[PDB]
Image (cartoon, coloured by chain):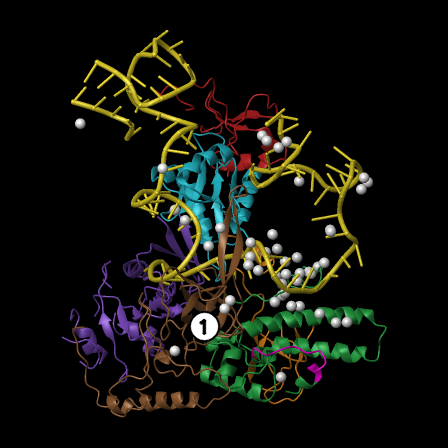
Chain colours: A brown, B purple, C orange, D cyan, E red, F green, G yellow
RNA sequence: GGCGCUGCUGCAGUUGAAACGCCCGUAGUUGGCCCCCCGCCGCCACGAGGAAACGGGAGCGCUCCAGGCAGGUUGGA
């Protein structure tokens, strides 16, 4: 890391995101409808009592492969052990793209992938599709029709082996087409 | 120096000096051979101003050694949809070769409207049709239009009359 | 006798349908008429089917007819 | 509706020559039709043509010299590997010595002899002989 | 010329005639085909012996009556008519 | 035309001039025919009739040749384009008329047949406009509600 | 296999067997012409990587042969 930190003079003020995260943590403590207190495993919970600010209050990482961390994950207040940026999982294996078929589950979506199958006797093709279940971190929000890029992780449920890592929005009320990519 | 945009690239000084319309100025005069040698460029958002009085303007120039055409300065863009990072920017349709080369042949003879084009496949050539009534006042200017069009587009061109 | 399709005779080309000509073109045209009581002159479409008035008159001076239109008591030209 | 402009052009040309006409008009025009007529011309099967502009889909006027036994298109445009060309040659062509199958490849439009001269494949669009 | 051997010799038995109008080959047993010849005067309104022009027409052009105009057009190209 | 919902096969149409230029007698500038277009649109004239009036009174063959744009685009540029395009509006009007005729005459099956044809055309065109972003994504033709939307 | 009597190449549907009584219409299939010199598919070519036997195929007289991998510096490409 050859270069070192150019000089803005509003940095320490702009770290008011510390009180932001702190009061979000203290709001989670008051929602007595919950049964478990949710917290990241990478973070002490004694760093919140301190005032010198010297220690970070939220954990995040980079996933590699030229995919950059969204700022909504860096400055969010949610808890997700299955989020690839702020949870306890990793991305490795195949990386694919598809379209959102359904977003009706809890932090889970269905993805529709399209492809062609050649039949040699008839010298022609047929159009085919498959459905893939994927995990949706709160740092993204999607609707049906949007393009997504998903990447492989370890097994996460009976049907899920992938995680949403990029979103390309698609306007509502547009003609739905084959769109293989 | 107030009649041209470029400065200091100076083949014909005298055109700017003679042209001194008080609000108008030109750029980038050119010389094309082939007899009586020959093209004057103008900034695009003044063509409609220049073409207003252009029949009686070209006379007051044809500097008897040369012949003068008034054309607009037009940009041709290479790619449609340049993909710069995360987005694609769309090439304006007026900036293609097919549009600009069609505008040049219309501005080459502006007071007169061509009434037909054909492409002959004999090296392909272009045949341009004009109304017969105005056969005079173009008859002596046709070889200049053909040579200049080949110089600016490299298309063979012949002229016939309605 | 030897006709060339690339340079048809205009006379026998005008008698064909406007669309199956070599280069499609309109059949209509404009023309000048003179008001029967006013010195001036107005330019009128040859296939009009909408009101056309005098500069002075309030009586409509055209009769729509399903083809070329006729006129009431006026004398015409071609430009 | 109208789908294959090249098919209609070639049917019109074959009809006109079978009658014994000197010229024929085909409309509309297109880039593909001009490429097909250019190849037919360069092999010597037709004379001059002319594309006439109408600020629409243009017309073409074709001059005929009585050398065209048949011309057609292959729909759909099946793709052909380099080694299947000959299994197509003995299918469409009257012999192995004259006639032409036209392919589109990433090196342009070309006949089959040049396609095996550059040892590549492509997609078939038509044939004449 | 006709078909050639691999060395350069024509291995063709005979060459059919071609139509002067439609360039089609005549072929044997096409008994509607006609060859005919025109005088080519050239000499003060009187013909010259054994100096003619000669055309041929296949049966397809005759079966529809196309020859009356095509023969005329062919003649106007050889300086025998106008 | 006359061929989507019948066995017509008619070809009657207009063919515009090859040359794209003002008229020899054209005095008008774009800024002064835009004036007449906007005065006619404010008065309540539909865009297909504005072209008729400019053709028949002002001796202008094509508005595009004298301005460089088209009539509906100029209306849109001065904020005077309609909420609903003219052709869809006319089809809805004809549907309302046929339904109101059928309210007194329940034995007219020919009119019911033509009502079906008109409404099928309406749905197809509405889908076109919707996916093209010329109409709200929630636009829907409703037979029962169509009479009072014509006022707005 | 004969069999183009299963037809992608490549059948038949007026009368031999066979065009729904007709109109609308979703899924599906198909869709004129135009900008070239960007991106993403398909497609074509060439590579990398993974099994032999079988199947092709270079060389070799189990006396020939079906074989086999021999052999007189070699070889199983
Ligand atoms: K988290
Ligand atoms: K695919
Ligand atoms: K497959
Ligand atoms: K399919
Ligand atoms: K689970
Ligand atoms: K599960
Ligand atoms: K599809
Ligand atoms: K006709
Ligand atoms: K007509
Ligand atoms: K008429
Ligand atoms: K129909
Ligand atoms: K009809
Ligand atoms: K018809
Ligand atoms: K009904
Ligand atoms: K109905
Ligand atoms: K419908
Ligand atoms: K309906
Ligand atoms: K539709
Ligand atoms: K519909
Ligand atoms: K309305
Ligand atoms: K069989
Ligand atoms: K078989
Ligand atoms: K067989
Ligand atoms: K059949
Ligand atoms: K039966
Ligand atoms: K039966
Ligand atoms: K029967
Ligand atoms: K049927
Ligand atoms: K059926
Ligand atoms: K039906
Ligand atoms: K239907
Ligand atoms: K339909
Ligand atoms: K459908
Ligand atoms: K579909
Ligand atoms: K199908
Ligand atoms: K499809
Ligand atoms: K279709
Ligand atoms: K491929
Ligand atoms: K290729
Ligand atoms: K092995
Ligand atoms: K060795
Ligand atoms: Mg007509
Ligand atoms: Mg239909
Ligand atoms: Mg029709
Ligand atoms: Mg008509
Ligand atoms: Mg069989």
Viewer-side residue, E30 vs C71: E30
Left or right: C1, with B92 as reference point: right
> Residue C4, can we see it?
no
Reply yes or no: does residue F141 show up in magenta.
Answer: yes
Q: Nearer the viewer, residue D60 or A48?
A: A48
The answer to whether B140 is drawn above or below residue C55 in the figure is above
Q: Residue C69, how many percent across, how many down? A: 66, 73
| Residue located at (40% from left, 74% from top) | A81
CB at disc 1 and ligand 1 closer than 8 Å: no
In the depicted structure, whether residue E74 falls above or below residue F61: above
Find numbered disc 1 in the image and state the secondary structure of the residue it sits on.
loop
| Chain letter of the residue carrying label 1 | A
Q: Percent from the top left, x then y, of residue A128?
A: 53, 55
Relative depth, front residue between F42 and B39: F42
- Quadrant holding ligand 22? top right
Relative to D38, is A59 on the left or the right?
left
Residue G57 found in image quarter: top left
Q: For the stretch drawn in magenta, what is the main secondary structure?
A: loop
Position of D93 with respect to G61 (left or right) is: right
Magenta highlight on residue F7 = no
The answer to which image quadrant residue A173 occupies is bottom right
How many residues crowd around disc 1 within 10 Å: few (fewer than 14), some, or many (20 or more)?
many
Q: Position of residue D65 (x, y in %)?
A: 48, 38
Q: What residue is shown with label 1?
A: A136
- Write the residue at 19% across / 82% down: A6
Disc tally is 1
Between residue F59 and residue F91, name the one nearer to us. Answer: F91
Q: Residue furthest left?
A: B8
Q: On the rendered image, what quadrant is the N terminus of chain E found in? A: top left
- Find the magenta span and give its range: F136-147
């Amino acid at each position: 890391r050859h270069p070192l930190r150019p000089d803005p003079d509003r940095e320490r003020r702009a770290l008011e995101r510390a009180e932001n995260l702190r009061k979000a943590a203290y709001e989670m403590a008051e929602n007595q409808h919950e049964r478990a207190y949710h917290k990241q495993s990478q973070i002490f919970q004694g760093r919140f009592l301190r005032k010198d600010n010297a220690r970070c209050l939220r954990f995040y990482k980079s996933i590699g492969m030229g995919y950059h961390t969204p700022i909504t994950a860096i400055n969010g207040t949610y808890i997700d052990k299955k989020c690839p940026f702020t949870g306890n999982v990793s991305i490795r294996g195949r990386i694919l793209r598809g379209v959102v078929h359904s977003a009706k589950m809890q932090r889970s979506i269905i993805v529709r992938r399209d492809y062609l199958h050649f039949v040699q006797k008839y010298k022609r093709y047929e159009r085919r599709h498959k459905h893939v279940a994927a995990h949706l971190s709160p740092c993204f929000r999607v609707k049906e029709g949007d393009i997504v890029t998903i990447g492989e992780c370890r097994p996460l449920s009976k049907t899920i082996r992938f995680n949403v890592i990029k979103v390309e929005p698609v306007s509502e009320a547009a003609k739905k087409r084959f769109s293989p990519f | 120096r107030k009649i041209r945009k470029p400065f200091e690239s100076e083949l014909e000084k005298q055109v700017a000096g003679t042209l001194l319309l008080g609000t108008l100025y030109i750029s980038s005069v050119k010389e094309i051979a082939v007899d009586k040698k020959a093209v004057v460029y103008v900034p695009y958002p003044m063509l409609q101003s220049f073409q207003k009085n252009s029949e009686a303007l070209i006379l007051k120039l044809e500097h008897s050694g040369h012949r003068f055409i008034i054309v607009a300065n037009r940009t041709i863009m290479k790619n449609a949809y340049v993909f710069t990072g995360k987005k694609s920017i769309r090439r304006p349709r007026s900036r293609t070769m097919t549009s600009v080369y069609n505008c040049i042949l219309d501005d080459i003879c502006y007071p007169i409207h061509v009434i037909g084009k054909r492409t002959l496949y004999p090296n392909p050539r272009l045949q341009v049709v004009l109304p017969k009534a105005v056969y005079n006042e173009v008859s002596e200017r046709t070889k200049t239009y053909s040579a200049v069009y080949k110089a600016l587009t490299e298309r063979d061109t012949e002229f016939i009359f309605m | 006798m030897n006709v060339d399709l690339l340079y048809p005779d205009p006379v026998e080309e005008q008698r064909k349908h406007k669309l199956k000509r070599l280069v499609q073109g309109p059949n209509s045209y404009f023309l000048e008429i003179k008001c029967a009581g006013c010195q001036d002159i107005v330019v009128v479409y040859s296939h009009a089917n909408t009101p056309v008035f005098c500069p002075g008159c309030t009586s409509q001076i055209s009769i729509p007819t399903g083809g070329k239109c006729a006129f009431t008591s006026q004398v015409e030209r071609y430009r | 509706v109208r789908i294959n402009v090249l098919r209609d052009a070639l049917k019109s040309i074959c009809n006109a020559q079978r009658i014994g006409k000197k010229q024929v008009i085909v409309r509309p025009s297109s880039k593909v039709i001009i490429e097909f007529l250019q190849l037919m011309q360069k092999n010597g099967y037709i004379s001059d043509f002319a594309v006439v502009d109408n600020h629409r889909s243009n017309r073409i006027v074709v001059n005929l010299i009585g050398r065209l036994n048949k011309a057609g298109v292959i729909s759909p445009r099946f793709d052909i590997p380099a080694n299947d060309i000959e299994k197509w040659v003995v299918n469409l062509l009257p012999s192995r010595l004259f006639g032409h199958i036209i392919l589109t490849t990433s090196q342009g439009i070309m006949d089959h002899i040049e396609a095996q001269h550059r040892q590549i494949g492509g997609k078939v669009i038509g044939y004449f002989y | 010329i006709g078909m050639k051997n691999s060395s350069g010799v024509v291995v063709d038995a005979y060459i059919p005639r071609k139509c002067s109008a439609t360039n089609r080959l005549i072929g044997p047993k096409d008994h509607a085909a006609v060859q005919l010849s025109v005088a080519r005067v050239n000499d003060k309104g009187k013909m010259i012996e054994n100096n003619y022009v000669t055309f041929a027409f296949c049966g397809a052009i005759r079966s529809r009556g196309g020859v009356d105009s095509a023969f005329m057009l062919l003649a106007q190209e050889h300086g025998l008519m106008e | 035309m006359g061929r989507m919902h019948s066995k017509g096969k008619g070809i009657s149409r207009s063919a515009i001039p090859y040359t794209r230029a003002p008229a020899p007698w054209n005095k008008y500038t774009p800024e002064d025919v835009c004036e007449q277009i906007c005065k006619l649109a404010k008065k309540g004239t539909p865009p297909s009739r504005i072209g008729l009036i400019l053709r028949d009174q002002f001796a202008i063959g094509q508005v595009k040749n004298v301005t460089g744009s088209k009539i509906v685009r100029i209306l849109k540029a001065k904020g005077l384009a309609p909420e609903i395009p003219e052709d869809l509006y006319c089809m809805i009007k004809k549907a309302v008329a046929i339904r109101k005729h059928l309210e007194r005459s329940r034995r007219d099956k020919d009119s019911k047949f033509r009502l079906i044809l008109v409404e099928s055309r309406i749905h197809r065109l509405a889908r076109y406009y919707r996916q093209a972003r010329r109409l709200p994504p929630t636009f829907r033709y409703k037979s029962d509600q169509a009479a009072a939307l014509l006022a707005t």
